[PDB]
Structures are given as C-alpha cells and as structure tokens.
Amino acid sequence: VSPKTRTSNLKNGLTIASESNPLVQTATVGVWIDAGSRNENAYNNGTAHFFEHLAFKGTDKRSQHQLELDIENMGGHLNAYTSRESTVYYAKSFKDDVPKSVEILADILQHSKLAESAIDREREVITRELEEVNKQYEEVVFDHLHATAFMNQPLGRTILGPRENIQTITNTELRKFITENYTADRMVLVGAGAVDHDALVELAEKYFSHLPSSQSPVPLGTPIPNFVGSEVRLRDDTMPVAHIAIAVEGVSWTSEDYYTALVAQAIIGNYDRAVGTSRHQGSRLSNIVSENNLANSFQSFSTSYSDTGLWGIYLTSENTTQIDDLVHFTLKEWNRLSTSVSNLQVERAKSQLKAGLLLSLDGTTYVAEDIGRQLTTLGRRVTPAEVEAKLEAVTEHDVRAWAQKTLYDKDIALVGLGPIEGLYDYNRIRNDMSMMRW
Amino acid sequence: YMGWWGHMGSPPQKGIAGYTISPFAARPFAGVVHAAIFNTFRRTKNQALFVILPVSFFYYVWTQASEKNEWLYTKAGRHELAKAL
Image (cartoon, rainbow over all chains, first blue to last red; front, side, top):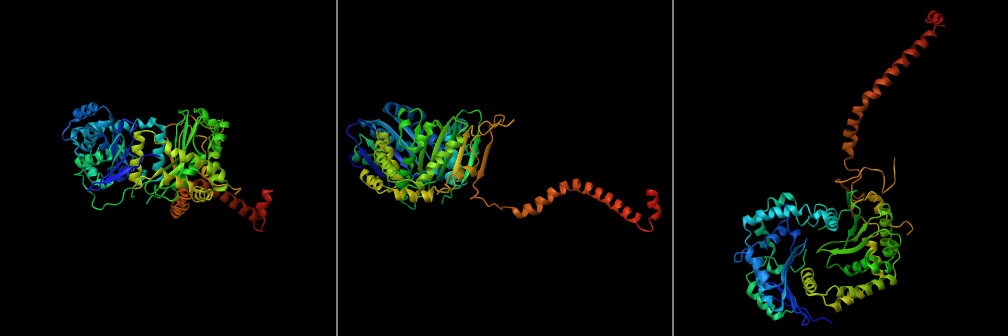
C-alpha cells in the first residue's frame, strides 16, 4: 500500500499535489497544465508547441546561457512536452536541489523573454521538425488518425501546426496564449519521490503566488467532437513495413464506461514477435497472428480526452500479401467482444489490469506523471482501492453492452502507411465490423 | 499482366495520399440534381455528333430506298420497275 497523495491549494487556485517515497534519493517536481494544442484556433495552431521551445530560450533574469548553466549546476535535468489537451514542464533532481528546480520552473513559465530574435531563430528549427517527424511512423499514423477522425475540429489539428503559422507566429500571440491558458486554476504543481509536501507548498507560495486566476474558474479536466468514419491511405511501396491504425470513437476520462473500455482493450491486448513470451499469450488475436505470421506487432489502445476518445489498434506487418487476413482476423476478434465474450475472458483481463495499473508506476517520473494526469483530467488522484473497486465492477454483461454500442457495426477511422496495396477499400474493412452469422 | 492483392503489378507508388469518408457519413445523392441536369447535358452535348451523323445518314439512305421501292410497285412506277428488273 503506497503512501497517500497529499493535496493543497493556494489562494490563486494553484493545486499542489505530492507523493513522498523515503526509499529514493531523487525527486521529480513539475507543473502539469490543463491546456494544450486544442486551445488554439486555426490561425495560431502551433503556438503551444512554439512556446515550449522558447521557454528554454531565456528569461528576464537568466539568459539562454545562464539558464543552461543553472540547470547543469543543479545536476539533474528539465523536460517538457505539449499534447492536445495537456502541457507538462518538470525537473528531475536530487532531494535537496528541489528548491532550485521549482525556482527555475517558475521563472521559465512566468518570466520568459520571447525575444523577436529567438522567435526568428526557432522558426527555422521548427520548420525542420516538419520534415523529420516523417520518419517516426507511429506518430505519422496517429497524427493522420486524429486528423481524419476529428475532421476539421480542434482535436484533429496537429501539435506542430501548419508551415504557414510557423512563419507568422509573433511574440504577441505567444504571450496572449500563455496569459489566457497558463492560469493558476489550470495548473498543478506536482512532486514525487524525495519531496516534503509542506516544503513544496512553501515553494509554491514563494514562486507561483503571483499567477493570474482565470475569470471563470471551471473544475480541472473540464472540456462537441463529431467523429468521422473515414480513411487516409499513405501508400509507399518502397517501405518494407505496413503501419495500420483502426479506431472507433472511444471514451472520455470521466465516462462511466472508462474501465469497461480498458478491460475490452486488454482482452485483445498487445503482441510483438520480438518478445519471447508473446507467442504464448492468452489473447485469441495474439494466437492467430503469431501462428500465421500475420504481423510484427500490434498494440491495442484506448486514448481518452476530456470529451471523447479513440479506441482501436495499431498494427505493423511485413506480410504484404496477407494484410487482408490480418485486418479480417483483428476485426473478427472485435466482433467477439459483442457476440461471444464471457466471464472467462473478462475475469482474465481484470486480473491482468489490476496489476498493470499499479506496475506502470515504477519511478518518480511515472508517479509524477500519474498524479499530474489524474489531477488535470479528473480533478483528484484516484486511490488504488477505488480503482480496484471500479475494475471489479466490470462484468461480462458490461463488456458486451459496451461493445455492442461502440464497436458493433460502427464506422471506423482507418490509416494505412507503407506497402498497403493489400489493404482493401473502406467498405470491405467496415463490413468486418459486424458478423452476418450473428 | 495482372498480379493479385499485394503484388498487383503497379509501378512503385509513392507520394499520393488518398482520403475518403464512410458510406454512412456521406449523403449518397449529394449534388444529384446538378449532375442529372448539367453533368448529363455536358456529357451528351460532347458526344452528340458521333451519334447524330451516322444515324441520320443511314436513316436518310433507308428512307430514300424504301420510298423508291414503294413507288416502283405502284401503277405510276410500272415502267421504271420494268427497266429496274
């Protein structure tokens, strides 16, 4: 039984949340913000990601070089990432270097220069990033997947933004973005590892007390997405591996079906020919795929947002003449979540998940990421006892009912990249979303 | 000259992104009235000569032949029939 997550607020409405571990000697402190690319419009799309670059380009006190030196002298590192709904800025350090790291984070968030010279310099760096994501096939597939599933909607936009915006982003719009979005009621200061909660609250009172509050404070993790059944094909005969994602509209963080969708996802599970144990997994799809050499890997996913989600599978295969079989067998395993699953699969998946949700948190950065994610999506850290109860409440009837309303005979978003000549047209893929025998 | 799915015999394809939407998401009869009137008119206008010229020529030939044949077998056409046979 893990130590209790302590939570305090400041007057502005900044949440401080901590989980101490007296067995480690490092600490991860950082700021989780309930804001990301989705908060941009079409004209300033790319701003949030642009700011992330400039946050490390110098503040009103420390220059770019001084910033570098200060962190080098601390001994640990700083890291940041911007997603569609969430931005994170954290610092991993030694136990007693925590006050330094909180001070640096407070500086780069509140007091960043955003100097025209630096805007202009990064504008090329970010332009080069547009032509090099092209290599990260999983990311290419998932970005096209969001773009098509949420066609012409904010969740459909990329994080980098269009080339056009990169050339026209000004310090004015950068400043406007972080003034509107980086408000105290949207921010959580998180500490995990060798942190004292009371010490962290004091550091918050010292550095984050002059943060603006938003005019209308909504609760943390407050949001209408209209999913489009659709396909993007990026055929490239020169690539040896096909990458395919298939998804349906999934569940939000606060859906009542959140755990049901996780259990369903665990019934299909993951597979990777490179891992020794994968040929012995219990999942039916795993057995079909491994026996017939249909794929190098597959990974089931259930991505959530504040008001929607995507539930589906990502496949990679070199078997270019049997892509049809791979997709066919995958979707017939999904059909069985509607028609055939019983207590046998459901209780097996529950067993696997009860551990999986706890195992994931195996270092201070993972713990901080868990506290930060849960605080910015649900408004609270959910105790493992509550999570164990919600998983236990999932029955086979719940899984069947969920799959019959979410998967069965529903539109999919489909992205294929690589040698995908063998991937059939939309109708034949979508026809596998039901079974004529049932 | 044709293979099968996965090895159809296409030259290598690269650089084309294809997009489409679900049959359930689309209006199947979108733009039907415009198509039925303007598209059909364009397509028909551009092929009209290739039908009109041969049809009208062979119909004229037939009409002349059938009218002559009819006239040859009347009283008035007796003499011309006698020569024709």
